[PDB]
Image (cartoon, coloured by chain):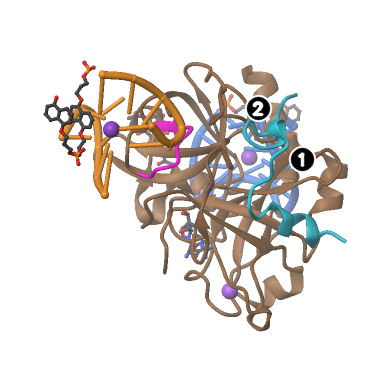
Chain colours: A brown, B cyan, C blue, D orange
Amino acid sequence: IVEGSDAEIGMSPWQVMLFRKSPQELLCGASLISDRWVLTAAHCLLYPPWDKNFTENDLLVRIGKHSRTRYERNIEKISMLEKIYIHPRYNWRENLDRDIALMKLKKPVAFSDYIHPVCLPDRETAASLLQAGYKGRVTGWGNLKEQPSVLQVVNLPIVERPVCKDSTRIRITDNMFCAGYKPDEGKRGDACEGDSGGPFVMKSPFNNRWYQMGIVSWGEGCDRDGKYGFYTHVFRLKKWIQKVIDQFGE
Amino acid sequence: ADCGLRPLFEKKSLEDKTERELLESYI
DNA sequence: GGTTGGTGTGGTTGG
DNA sequence: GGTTGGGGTTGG
Ligand SMILES: *[PH](O)(O)OCCCOc1cccc2c(OCCCOP(=O)(O)OCCCOc3cccc4c(O)cccc34)cccc12
Ligand SMILES: *[PH](O)(O)OCCCOc1cccc2c(OCCCOP(=O)(O)OCCCOc3cccc4c(O)cccc34)cccc12
Ligand SMILES: *C[C@@](*)(O)[C@H](CCCNC(N)=[NH2+])NC(=O)[C@@H]1CCCN1C(=O)[C@H](N)Cc1ccccc1
Ligand SMILES: *[C@@H]1O[C@H](CO)[C@@H](O[C@@H]2O[C@H](CO)[C@@H](O)[C@H](O)[C@H]2NC(C)=O)[C@H](O)[C@H]1NC(C)=O
Ligand SMILES: [K+]
Ligand SMILES: [K+]
Ligand code: NA
């Protein structure tokens, strides 16, 4: 997170750290959507151009964390993975279309002050919140520029499609949106490498609940003027999420 | 069913330092 | 079709 | 120091 600030405690209790076993390492962000299901970016798990390919037993998740490298005695809970479900139409070759994966944990996580799932949007929520100029919030432990000691947060406005399009040569699809301040706006901020998989969330002014509208997917550099962060469009992939969970069990 | 209401925030009727910026960005 | 679109027999992948 | 920096979001 570039040009963000330290999170307050229990500000983002659905935040999840994808943690590599050996060598021991932070890989990516993720989010908790129920007691046995975590949502992440597919490219965190599978990206052949970099020779990346992680299986269930290569990884752990850490939930309830604030500090980046300290084990938080009595706060955080660590879980093993039972199964990874990468979207079947993920496209790592071209433009990271459908950059999304679900992970089922081996055991249910007990909720607390510091561990709690985010809501996923429906049609109406999507239609009223995902609009240009509306701001959402991005969180993570990724790079502070083009490494922090506590979780970083930044608020960024959704950008209209034609501006997103004109900002990159990468082929944009309807499974993505972009966010960030325009050069002339003055305020600044972006996600960066290491933040992938983390949620773009918005608080509904109707029922005051936080909804995950996006997943940190890609960008070109970090916080460059006239460039914007790209996010997987969570509602557009909601039918797939409900299908996987309904079939494989909560 | 309990989703998206934070134990330290919404459940306590306390806000975080920056959510107001989000709310104001709507209409 | 599918846990999945269609340029529908491979492709960034089996059958 | 510890699974871990400098009470705390938690023992000793
Ligand atoms: P594994 O080794 O078991 O897989 C091989 C055997 C199963 O093969 C298939 C089963 C079902 C479908 C297909 C297939 O479908 C392609 C998409 C649809 O294409 P289309 O719109 O052109 O429809 C096909 C038109 C011709 O239909 C048939 C062709 C040959 C045989 C039969 C048949 O026996 C019954 C009905 C129709 C057809 C592509 C490849 C394999 C399989
Ligand atoms: P449980 O109840 O079985 O055991 C808990 C009792 C032991 O508690 C501690 C053990 C080790 C370290 C510390 C501690 O470390 C803080 C590091 C910073 O040092 P400082 O700046 O606080 O140094 C001040 C020195 C004060 O020394 C003492 C104070 C009181 C008692 C004693 C004593 O009995 C022997 C030697 C020194 C001191 C902080 C707190 C507890 C423990
Ligand atoms: C895996 C994630 O941590 C990371 C997030 C980057 C966020 N950037 C900004 N400024 N919001 N994503 C990446 O690193 C992705 C995955 C692989 C390469 N990549 C990129 O963003 C490239 N920099 C650009 C790109 C290459 C291939 C396909 C799409 C985009
Ligand atoms: C990523 O790694 C996994 C684990 O090695 C690969 O899964 C294996 O390879 C083939 C094809 O998927 C299958 O026989 C088995 O599922 C696994 N076999 C072994 C040897 O464990 C998978 O192929 C890799 N993914 C990609 C896209 O290359
Ligand atoms: K196919
Ligand atoms: K301590
Ligand atoms: Na920018």
Please name the residue shown 54% across and 51% down the image. A139
Q: Amino acid at mark 1?
A: Pro
Q: Pointer 1: what residue? A: A121
Residue A16 spot, x, y in % from top left: 50, 37
Say whether mark 2 is within 8 Å of ligand 5. Answer: no
Q: Quadrant of the C terminus of chain A?
A: top right
Residues rendered magenta in the picture: A60-68
Residue A94 magenta-highlighted: no
User: Would residue A78 be seen by someone viewing this image from the given angle?
Assistant: no
Task: Please indicate whether residue A16 sits to the left or right of residue A228 in the image.
Answer: left
Instruction: Name the mark on residue A244.
Output: 2
User: Would residue A223 be seen by someone viewing this image from the given angle?
Assistant: yes
Residue A74 spot, x, y in % from top left: 40, 24
Q: Amino acid at mark 2?
A: Val
Q: Give the class, few, some or many, for how many residues have Cα within 10 Å of label 1's Cα (few <14, many ≥20).
A: many
Name the residue nearer the viewer: A133 or A172.
A133
